[PDB]
Amino acid sequence: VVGGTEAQRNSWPSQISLQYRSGSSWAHTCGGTLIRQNWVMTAAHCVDRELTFRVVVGEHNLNQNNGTEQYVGVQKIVVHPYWNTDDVAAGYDIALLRLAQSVTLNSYVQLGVLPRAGTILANNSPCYITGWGLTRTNGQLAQTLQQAYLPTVDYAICSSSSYWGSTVKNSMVCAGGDGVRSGCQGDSGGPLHCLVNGQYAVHGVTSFVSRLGCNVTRKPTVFTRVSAYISWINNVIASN
Ligand SMILES: [Ca+2]
Image (cartoon, rainbow, N blue to C red):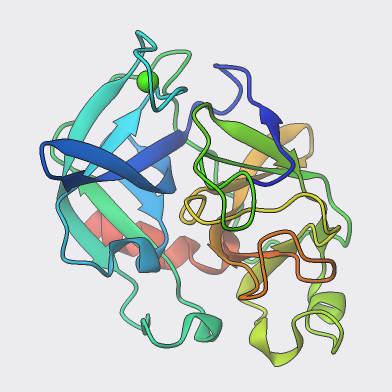
């Protein structure tokens, strides 16, 4: 997250760190949202590689013991069947991970609240992106979880020529684009939390930014629109 502030430890308890095995250690690669005690919602593109993955819940600082972490292997990966790795702009950038164990809920570990199917937010709706992604374009991952206030940019504006044009689909949510704050590599798969009727819900799964850079004016961060996939999500959990 570029232009973020450090999140309080208990603000976003559904945020997870998706990590891969790298030699004798584990490396953060993406975010995710805990949606059942044994299911995580993330981006399809985060799990294209043939890697070994684990999920960390209750995580705050990737580089130090927080006293709150639970580490769990990934047992099954269900990518949206229409996902195509060579075409992120087509959408469908969403995947569900079944965890090998059910995690224990507490102040640091909670299920993310999902929007009702079909819900579209009004332009300029208040949202926060969270994650441990790069804190600058071509920079390095955050140690501590970051948040940044990224108001939505509706489809009409986001798909206009000076924004993302045809690249953005109505199955996506755009947010930010102020040239200061943005998601960035390593935030992919994580939540966009938006305040609606007094309650934050996870409206987006972080998907992509400009090839030009993370914080680029009129290139808001783009997220898979969770509310476009509620039936798909329910169907997968029901059948697995
Ligand atoms: Ca830690």
